Amino acid sequence: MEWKRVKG
Amino acid sequence: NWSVEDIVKGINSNNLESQLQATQAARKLLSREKQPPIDNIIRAGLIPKFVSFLGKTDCSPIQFESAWALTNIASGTSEQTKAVVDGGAIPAFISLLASPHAHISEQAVWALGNIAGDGSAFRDLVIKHGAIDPLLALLAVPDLSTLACGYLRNLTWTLSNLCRNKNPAPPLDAVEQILPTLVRLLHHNDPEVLADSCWAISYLTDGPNERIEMVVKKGVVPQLVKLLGATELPIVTPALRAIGNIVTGTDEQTQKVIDAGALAVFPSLLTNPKTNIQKEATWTMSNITAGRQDQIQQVVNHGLVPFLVGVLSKADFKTQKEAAWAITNYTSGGTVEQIVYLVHCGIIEPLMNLLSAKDTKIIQVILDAISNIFQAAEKLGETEKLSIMIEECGGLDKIEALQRHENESVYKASLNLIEKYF
């Protein structure tokens, strides 16, 4: 699971 | 896209509307796929201004734009997440969880998940600032399906990051506070919510048996077993990790996995075309065969021994290593009849073939297994039948060679085998 996520 | 110089000029103006437009420009700049200039934005000193914009209740657009800008900074490296934390963003984001604007609340959820996801210390710092109560309050509706799907996925992901990381694991009180909501999300009909809830459970069961028990006591093992059978690989992967973690625990915890029907899924898992699923399924089996004789018997009754022979015969090498472990645990703990049955299903030849592996650990594990099987053959008086049999598939030669082998316990155990039985 992604640890950090960018909002594009 | 604006230049950083122009963003700074607008944010430094004495005009809220000019500040809003410059913050939006910062958000768009930080949102571009190739190489956002995060460090330039930080070096310009803009984080403290974004953080102060979070508190502008009278201007919800600049709250949203600055929240989004900070989310994308906090999604970067640990040093970039730290810069956001060091600007005071954690309590400002927690205050926005209660916002009447759903897009702002969601942005704050996202940001806190990025911060908590950075590591154990920031996770615990988010918890100390009081994030859990207002996060859980966002899910206090009678039917989760009335929530926007994206909103719900974001909340689930952030809760799973609060369950994540070790040394230390999350505070026990925080885990107990979050777990009833996780149980609910584990029954929600959305593939991404299910996947991330399974990941959260996988984190909470990755530890000592006391931690496993907190999860098992909520009664989720049958649902995890059901999710083991999902068609979506993003669901099966964390559900299998959670199940595999649980069977590292006590015999009684392992029994709840068996009682829930998990063994019926393992014919498919042990032949799964995704290498990592096969590996983790075989690892899981190796901890079940480390259990009681009646649990080994249930592995037998479910027809899983031929599948272990299969993965030992042909699989990715790391999976074959887990299969070797499963065999050594089976023969260490099993009855004579269980070991006879293992030999009748064909374990000897693939065991011996793996003695050619250039890996010291698997050779040790296999030699242990062979000795365990001889000890069963001794009790039956059939050591020579097994010896001839090792001989016929070429196992004697590969044991002979390891007399001439670097590692000490290898040639020690190899020597003893040939002396005693050959």
Image (cartoon, coloured by chain):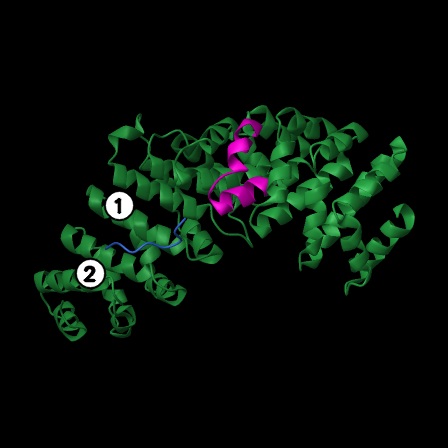
> B33 or B168, which lies in front?
B33
User: Which residue is denoted by mark 1 in the rendering?
Assistant: B106
Residue at figure coordinates x 59%, y 24% from the top left: B259
Give percent across and percent down for residue B303.
62, 27
Left or right placement of residue B53 versus residue B153 in this view:
left
Q: Residues within 10 Å of mark 2 (few under 14, many from 20)?
A: many
Is residue B47 placed above or below B219 in the rendered structure?
below
Chain identifier for the blue-coloured part of the image: A
Residue at figure coordinates x 55%, y 53% from the top left: B168
Tag on residue B209?
none
Residue B269 among magenta residues: yes
Report the number of discs: 2
- Marks 2 and 1 on same chain: yes
Left or right placement of residue B129 versus residue B175 in this view:
left
Q: Residues within 10 Å of mark 1 (few under 14, many from 20)?
A: many
Residue B59 among magenta residues: no
Q: Dot 1 lies on which element?
A: helix
Which contiguous range is marked in magenta? B263-282
Query: Which color was chain B given?
Result: green
Give percent across and percent down for residue B319.
58, 47
> In terms of image quadrants, where is residue B337?
top right
Left or right placement of residue B64 versus residue B92 in this view:
left
Q: Main secondary structure of the magenta part?
A: helix
Q: Dot 2 lies on which element?
A: helix
**Chain assignment, label 1:** B
Residue B115 visible in rendering: yes
User: Which residue is denoted by mark 2 in the rendering?
Assistant: B27
